[PDB]
Image: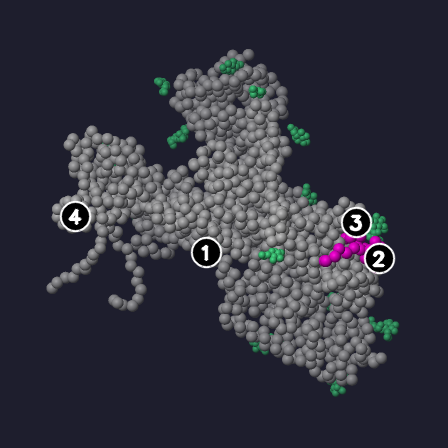
Amino acid sequence: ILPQGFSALEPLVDLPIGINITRFQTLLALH
Amino acid sequence: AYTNSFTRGVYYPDKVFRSSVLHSTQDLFLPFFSNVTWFHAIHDNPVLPFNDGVYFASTEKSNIIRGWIFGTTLDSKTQSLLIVNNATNVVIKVCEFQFCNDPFLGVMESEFRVYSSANNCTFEYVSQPFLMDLEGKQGNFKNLREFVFKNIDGYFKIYSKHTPILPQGFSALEPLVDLPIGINITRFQTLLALHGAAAYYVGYLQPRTFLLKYNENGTITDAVDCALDPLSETKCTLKSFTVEKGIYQTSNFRVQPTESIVRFPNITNLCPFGEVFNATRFASVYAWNRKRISNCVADYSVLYNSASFSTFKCYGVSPTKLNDLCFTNVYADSFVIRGDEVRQIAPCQTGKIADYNYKLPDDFTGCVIAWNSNNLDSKVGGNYNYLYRLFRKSNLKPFERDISTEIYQAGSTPCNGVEGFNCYFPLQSYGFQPTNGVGYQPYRVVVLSFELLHAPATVCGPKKSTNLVKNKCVNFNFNGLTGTGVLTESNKKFLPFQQFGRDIADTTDAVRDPQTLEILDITPCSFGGVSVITPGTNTSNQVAVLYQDVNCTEVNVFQTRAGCLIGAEHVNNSYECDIPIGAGICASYQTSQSIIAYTMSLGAENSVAYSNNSIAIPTNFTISVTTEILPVSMTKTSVDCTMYICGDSTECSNLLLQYGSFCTQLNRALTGIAVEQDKNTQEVFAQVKQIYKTPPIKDFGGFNFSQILPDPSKPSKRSFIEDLLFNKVTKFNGLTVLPPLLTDEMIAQYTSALLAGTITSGWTFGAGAALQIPFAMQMAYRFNGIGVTQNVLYENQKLIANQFNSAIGKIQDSLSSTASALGKLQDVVNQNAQALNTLVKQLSSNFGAISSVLNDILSRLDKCEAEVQIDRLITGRLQSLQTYVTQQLIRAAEIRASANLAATKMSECVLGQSKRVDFCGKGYHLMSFPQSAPHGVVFLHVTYVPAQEKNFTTAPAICHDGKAHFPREGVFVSNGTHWFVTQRNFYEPQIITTDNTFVSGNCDVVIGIVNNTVYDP
Amino acid sequence: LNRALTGIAVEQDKNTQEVFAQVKQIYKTPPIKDFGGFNFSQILPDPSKPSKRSFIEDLLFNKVTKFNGLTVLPPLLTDEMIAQYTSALLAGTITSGWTFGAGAALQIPFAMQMAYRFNGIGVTQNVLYENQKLIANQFNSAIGKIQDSLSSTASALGKLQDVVNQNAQALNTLVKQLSSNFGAISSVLNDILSRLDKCEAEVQIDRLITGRLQSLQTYVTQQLIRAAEIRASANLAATKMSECVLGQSKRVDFCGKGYHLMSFPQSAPHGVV
Amino acid sequence: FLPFQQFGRDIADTTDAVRDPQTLEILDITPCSFGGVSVITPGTNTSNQV
Amino acid sequence: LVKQLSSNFGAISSVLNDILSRLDKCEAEVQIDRLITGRLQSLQTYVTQQ
Ligand SMILES: *[C@@H]1O[C@H](CO)[C@@H](O[C@@H]2O[C@H](CO)[C@@H](O)[C@H](O)[C@H]2NC(C)=O)[C@H](O)[C@H]1NC(C)=O
Ligand SMILES: *[C@@H]1O[C@H](CO)[C@@H](O[C@@H]2O[C@H](CO)[C@@H](O)[C@H](O)[C@H]2NC(C)=O)[C@H](O)[C@H]1NC(C)=O
Ligand SMILES: *[C@@H]1O[C@H](CO)[C@@H](O[C@@H]2O[C@H](CO)[C@@H](O)[C@H](O)[C@H]2NC(C)=O)[C@H](O)[C@H]1NC(C)=O
Ligand SMILES: *[C@@H]1O[C@H](CO)[C@@H](O[C@@H]2O[C@H](CO)[C@@H](O)[C@H](O)[C@H]2NC(C)=O)[C@H](O)[C@H]1NC(C)=O
Ligand SMILES: *[C@@H]1O[C@H](CO)[C@@H](O[C@@H]2O[C@H](CO)[C@@H](O)[C@H](O)[C@H]2NC(C)=O)[C@H](O)[C@H]1NC(C)=O
Ligand SMILES: *[C@@H]1O[C@H](CO)[C@@H](O[C@@H]2O[C@H](CO)[C@@H](O)[C@H](O)[C@H]2NC(C)=O)[C@H](O)[C@H]1NC(C)=O
Ligand SMILES: *[C@@H]1O[C@H](CO)[C@@H](O)[C@H](O)[C@H]1NC(C)=O
Ligand SMILES: *[C@@H]1O[C@H](CO)[C@@H](O)[C@H](O)[C@H]1NC(C)=O
Ligand SMILES: *[C@@H]1O[C@H](CO)[C@@H](O)[C@H](O)[C@H]1NC(C)=O
Ligand SMILES: *[C@@H]1O[C@H](CO)[C@@H](O)[C@H](O)[C@H]1NC(C)=O
Ligand SMILES: *[C@@H]1O[C@H](CO)[C@@H](O)[C@H](O)[C@H]1NC(C)=O
Ligand SMILES: *[C@@H]1O[C@H](CO)[C@@H](O)[C@H](O)[C@H]1NC(C)=O
Ligand SMILES: *[C@@H]1O[C@H](CO)[C@@H](O)[C@H](O)[C@H]1NC(C)=O
Ligand SMILES: *[C@@H]1O[C@H](CO)[C@@H](O)[C@H](O)[C@H]1NC(C)=O
Ligand SMILES: *[C@@H]1O[C@H](CO)[C@@H](O)[C@H](O)[C@H]1NC(C)=O
Ligand SMILES: *[C@@H]1O[C@H](CO)[C@@H](O)[C@H](O)[C@H]1NC(C)=O
Ligand SMILES: *[C@@H]1O[C@H](CO)[C@@H](O)[C@H](O)[C@H]1NC(C)=O
Ligand SMILES: *[C@@H]1O[C@H](CO)[C@@H](O)[C@H](O)[C@H]1NC(C)=O
Ligand SMILES: *[C@@H]1O[C@H](CO)[C@@H](O)[C@H](O)[C@H]1NC(C)=O
């Protein structure tokens, strides 16, 4: 390069984690 | 030496009596006209292979041929069947026989050396005595003794036929004893006696379909080998031994693969199953382990053949196919459970294991492997290292794990650190002791979860790969995905995670080769329908074959766009179409004689001598009579859906009630049809309010109607022609035919009334009352109605009557000669009979049931298990009826349209005179006459056809005194010296006067105006 | 089912034969087109084409637009043969009026043919001759508008295109049905066989058949009904050909709006104009 | 029936005739007479006689 | 067409909600496909007749 346009997302690894996920967080780095 | 098997090797397929019926069966028979090896023996006999069954025959004069030997090695290492017929007592033994280098029985007999030992013998049978030839005696052969020997699932079936006398002829072989020998037979030998010439014949069976024709006495008298040649294939396809001229679709050509192609990823490392199945420690079921198996060669036959497993259930897959199939990944979910809980590790189970500790998807593909444990997983004082989840607030989703030591508040008491009432731990542990019962001892269970292929495969079975061959039809297997087709290079670009391509039908369009990452298109190898082009079998049995939409290279020989036609010679000359091929090509049987193929002619080439001042005016005419045949009705069938589906069975009827109103709505539809058949008949014939009669004296101006009016001397007052029509057109399963409301006599009376009205009153009986008129005057009006002045009839009345009478005579001669005249009504009859015959035969179908006979199910199964087989038969008999009824409704609609057309013609052709071109026959319509016919009506259309013409010069108008004179009716013509005005459809020149022409304008506007004079009376 | 579809294919050729092949001979126009000012160059064959079709026919053909055991059989009468039949019908109509229908083709000047057609509608024939030049120009202009209309928008042939679309649509539906599971583990028959031994497999396969047969029965039933509709249309077309082109129709709005004079057939893909 | 044949069949695969197991004679099996029953009635506003 | 909804077609009940409220999904799948196998035929019959 939200930008305007179209793009399909390809698959990456399929991980058999088996965990019940209800929460999320992203990770940012600190200077 | 070899000979041609001249119509031999057919046996009675079963033990059911049949008569006057053609029955189709597929089993191992010797094909007609095959080559058979012929051996003769003067005064020795080779060992032959036993493929899938052998046909044997012999001609005898001294009974040299005695018996047969069957087995695999015939040397005492395996069991071997020995059959000997030594002119007196048939002896059958199954022993581990030691055979001699040259087996024989002496001929007075002085030897017995067919075998040398008996050991570990399992079967012996000896028949009663008889007498046969025993001495050496020469001459000509008197007894042909034919046999068939085959082994199906351990039953050794012997068929035979004895007849007085390869000879030409036909003879079916009846069954003899059925012996449960259970031996794998790969080899054969015959047995000859040693001292006299004694020939015998050996043939071989291949899987064939045969059509057997049973005669009136129930003996098979002929047969068609449905896989012999195109004519036999056509005969078998139509279930008849006679084929009419035309083109039939009998089969489908399919190119077969030449070699198999097996392609797999080139990995040779073996998969770590031992570290899973023989692991030191299994995880607990609340915290089961999941090892991913990838990048290896797996072998599930070792795990499968091993007897150590207690239970083995595969869902979606079968254990013997796992060796060929391969996967993107395999997961081994490993844990220990209690024995009685093994049942819960399965799709669609619930319980303390299935909901809380290990849930499988209900759409699960893979295998559940389990075995008991009592060495490792159990101790004295119990094994308390195994924990399971005993309480959870909600169940588990498929393959979710959830480790948690949070003490479970069963109620509303928030204990939050201390166990109590309604506050327990979710993890519980049961112990395992060697003294516990079967259901409470530990079992080690591993479930193998398979992801079936959608991505590059990494876990494949021990099946070895092969080399790849391009541009040939092959039977391929790419990573477990199988199919047949030609592999070619392609220019498609699969992106790296995509392995397979698909077509609209979800079939594979292209694949990426697992060894070399290139894209290969998969196009199934060329195929197409095969049509047989044949003259009727009463002329010739020679045929031509059309291979549809192929070039013939893939298959004297002529390539057309309909396909490549073989056996028909291409002829440059065009003719009228006979047997259509397609794409403009027709074939026929012509001249010694052979089948020809040609481009269809569209008619003779003609040009019209057009000019701006030339008109052709007819000078003579012909009265023609043509026959138009229309269906009016079809047989009023009625089907009792209950007796058909559930004949005389309460159990079935009660099951049928679970399908609701399907019966009464089918009975309703058929009733509606039967009613419309009577309405159709009523609309076509009953439009006349009174029954009219002709006078006893037939003074109709020379027109002879004696062949269309009723003849009082018959038991049914039909016309002569009607009798001819009736002589040309030709129930205990709940299927009936209702009679029509209007009998043939009543129809004849209606047509008689219509004819008498037409003859004596013209069109007046249609509009209102029948007003008598002389027939000649009626014709005068009909001629006037077509633009021919009435005087033409009167001046030529005698000629016209003779032409009419002659035309009628030709109709009788035509109708009296060939059967094909009534084909439109006969096809309707044939279609209805055919629909019913199909419907009746469908009762013989199983539809997946154990038997087509409903009573045989009920007499063998108790009601509850029986319910499945019976609903399955209903599920098929109902479809057969729905198909039949739907086809009848569509066909009835076609008949209704035809009947409506017939009624329209009756109204406009017979009752009036039609100005609609070619509606009431070709030519200018005069009159029509109805005649009845079986399930239809025949109209005799009387038409005026111009016969002879001359070239006359014309002009659109004539100038006189500067005025332009135009015809009132007719055209101006000139014979080269004088101008006349005449009627268009009959040359009759008249002097041009002011009373035949009219004046409008001035002769300076009109294109083509000519000079003349007009006489003024 | 093979029988029902064969019956349909046969009726498609009979329908074509009934509409176009009612003339016993192949007629031809003279090389000199002296038809009283009526210009037929746009409906008569032009010898310079690889297929002897009229200009308008080419316009019609430019507007109307297999490995699962599904095939299409060719018609018996090729487009060229249809064009020859329509050419013969046009040449007959132009040079002999209605006489070629009843019997032999009797030549007549075109202007006289029109004189009869005008007389047939209650207009005295002198009206044509006095106004013959005007009439020819209006005819020629009307023909030009037909080409311009046909040459401009795609929608002119919608009745034939819908038939084509319906048949393609029926086949596309039929092909897609092979992708359906019908309760089976997989829509791909080979994938069932390569994974299950015969006996357990028998259930999945009968289940797929139980659905592929229904798809065919539905298709065939719809084709029989649609074929009946086409047959009715073909019968109507044959009736018009007989009463509109070969004769002159007194039936109101049967052969177009207005008082009918003449009609001209032109071939089109899977139909007649 | 020829000696190994015990049963006969119709087109519908129903039995047409059987050979009696005690006396080896052939007996035809024709299902006993049956047929539809139709009710002929004036409308019920006139009469309930049928 | 409306009455055909009351038919069982071999199922335990003609009422779809009564199957779902009584059987878990997996065993239920058989009874439901069985009801569909019949409601579809009823519609196909209706549509064909129409
Ligand atoms: C029946 O017996 C024959 C022996 O005549 C078996 O054929 C042998 O099969 C093995 C395995 O493929 C080959 O290595 C041998 O060479 C074959 N023998 C001959 C003479 O060719 C046959 O497999 C047996 N069939 C069954 C089902 O047991
Ligand atoms: C019109 O045609 C009819 C036959 O269609 C002619 O009648 C024939 O005349 C010849 C004389 O040359 C006789 O030999 C035949 O026997 C007649 N046949 C019949 C059936 O009558 C008639 O003469 C023709 N008229 C004209 C004027 O040409
Ligand atoms: C109407 O035609 C029939 C023939 O279809 C005539 O009957 C024939 O008459 C002749 C006498 O001229 C007999 O020799 C034939 O045997 C009769 N045939 C039949 C079948 O009856 C009948 O005479 C004709 N009508 C008139 C008034 O002449
Ligand atoms: C055109 O028709 C007229 C009228 O019949 C013919 O004139 C007659 O010819 C015959 C002999 O040729 C004479 O005997 C008559 O007297 C003529 N009629 C009159 C009124 O003069 C004329 O010949 C015909 N022309 C041709 C070329 O056939
Ligand atoms: C028909 O006759 C008329 C009158 O006799 C002709 O009219 C004459 O035509 C010539 C040549 O075109 C003119 O020069 C005269 O002036 C015309 N006279 C009149 C009174 O109109 C006419 O041409 C003739 N037509 C034919 C075909 O012969
Ligand atoms: C019939 O109409 C065509 C047009 O559709 C005429 O052909 C045109 O003739 C003119 C000359 O006047 C040329 O300039 C055009 O280029 C031609 N167009 C085509 C498409 O050929 C034809 O000449 C007309 N016929 C007559 C006898 O005039
Ligand atoms: C046996 O068949 C072969 C090939 O079909 C043929 O060439 C040979 O002549 C046949 N034997 C006899 C005796 O005709
Ligand atoms: C044929 O073999 C049987 C086998 O037991 C024997 O009893 C019989 O005598 C033999 N027939 C001869 C030697 O003619
Ligand atoms: C078969 O023959 C052998 C000969 O040595 C004998 O030992 C054996 O007991 C016999 N029976 C079986 C069943 O093998
Ligand atoms: C066989 O058919 C013939 C027909 O001519 C008949 O006479 C005969 O009685 C039938 N039965 C037998 C056993 O021949
Ligand atoms: C082994 O796999 C590689 C991968 O592309 C391939 O190139 C090579 O030819 C294979 N070897 C054999 C012997 O098939
Ligand atoms: C487990 O051990 C036994 C005995 O050592 C062996 O026969 C078996 O093959 C092993 N399991 C696997 C998967 O190899
Ligand atoms: C067979 O057909 C030919 C010609 O169609 C006919 O002449 C002959 O009589 C027919 N034979 C039979 C037995 O139908
Ligand atoms: C028939 O085969 C030839 C030979 O390869 C090929 O050139 C031709 O295009 C094929 N198809 C035809 C003639 O329609
Ligand atoms: C038929 O015509 C073709 C023209 O392409 C010619 O090649 C062929 O030899 C002709 N056949 C005969 C038998 O005259
Ligand atoms: C009319 O004249 C043309 C040309 O002179 C000729 O070909 C045609 O056969 C003639 N017609 C008759 C019926 O004589
Ligand atoms: C048409 O008629 C005109 C006179 O009206 C004449 O000059 C012309 O030559 C005629 N046509 C032919 C082809 O002769
Ligand atoms: C016993 O069977 C024979 C065989 O035909 C039969 O004739 C006899 O009547 C039977 N006896 C009884 C008592 O049924
Ligand atoms: C019943 O039918 C009769 C005759 O058709 C009519 O007169 C009468 O009014 C009808 N009654 C009712 C209640 O419809």
Q: Which residue is mark 3?
A: B711
Report whether mark 4 lies on the same chain as mark 3. Answer: yes
Classify mark 3: residues with Cα within 10 Å, few (<14), some (14-19) or many (20+). some
Classify mark 2: residues with Cα within 10 Å, few (<14), some (14-19) or many (20+). few
Choose between C4 and B879: the one closer to the eye.
Answer: B879
Nearer to us: label 1 or label 2: 2
Q: Chain of mark 3?
A: B
Report whether mark 1 lies on the same chain as mark 2. Answer: no
Choose between B663 and D29: the one closer to the eye.
Answer: B663
- Respond yes or no on whether mark 1 lies under 8 Å from ligand 14: no
Q: Which residue is mark 2?
A: B699
Q: Which residue is mark 4?
A: B406
Q: Chain of mark 1?
A: C
- Respond yes or no on whether mark 4 lies under 8 Å from ligand 12: no
Q: Which badge, 4 or 3, comes first in the chain's sequence?
A: 4
Q: Chain of mark 2?
A: B
Q: Which amino acid, by three-letter code, is at mark 1?
A: Asn
- Residue at left offset 65%, top offset 60%: C22
Q: Chain of mark 4?
A: B
Q: Are marks 4 and 3 in contact (CB under 8 Å)?
A: no
